[PDB]
Amino acid sequence: GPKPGDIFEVELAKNDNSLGICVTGGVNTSVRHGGIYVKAVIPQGAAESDGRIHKGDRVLAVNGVSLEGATHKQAVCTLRNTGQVVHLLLEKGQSPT
Ligand SMILES: *CC(=O)Nc1ccc(/N=N/c2ccc(NC(=O)C*)c(S(=O)(=O)O)c2)cc1S(=O)(=O)O
Image 1 (spheres, helix red, strand yellow):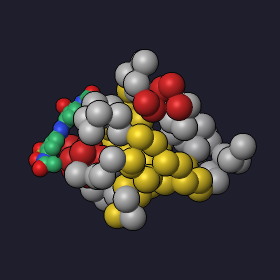
Image 2 (cartoon, rainbow, N blue to C red; image 1 turned 30 degrees about the horizontal axis):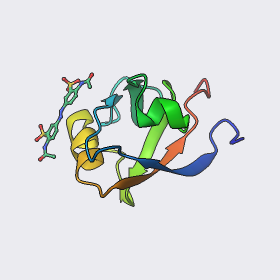
Image 3 (tube, rainbow, N blue to C red; image 1 turned 30 degrees about the vertical axis):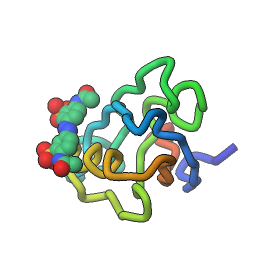
C-alpha cells in the first residue's frame, strides 16, 4: 500500500450524491500536517465500506483543488460540490509528524 507520507489518489463514490463525512484541521491549525484530517468516517458508508479512507488519514486535494489551507468547513463544502464520484488525494496521516 501507500507508505507513510505517500500521496495516493482514490476514487470514491459519494453514494446517492450525498456524503456526510467529517473532518478537522485545514487552516494549518493544531493538526500535525495542518491538513484536513479525517475526523470521523461514518460506518456503512462508501468511505468505510470501500476502505479507501480511515480515520487519521488526511485529505490533500479534493477534485484537484489544493485543499490545504482551506478550512474544515470549506473542506466538506468542497467534498459536497463534487460530481458522482469524488476524486481526492489522500496522504497517509499515520505518519507521526
Ligand atoms: C462532520 C463533523 O463532525 N463536523 C462538521 C460537518 C460539517 C460542517 N460544515 N459544513 C459546510 C457545508 C457547506 C458549506 N458551504 C457551501 O456552500 C459548500 C459550509 S460553509 O459555507 O460554512 O463553509 C459548511 C462543519 C462541521 S464542524 O466540525 O462543526 O465545523
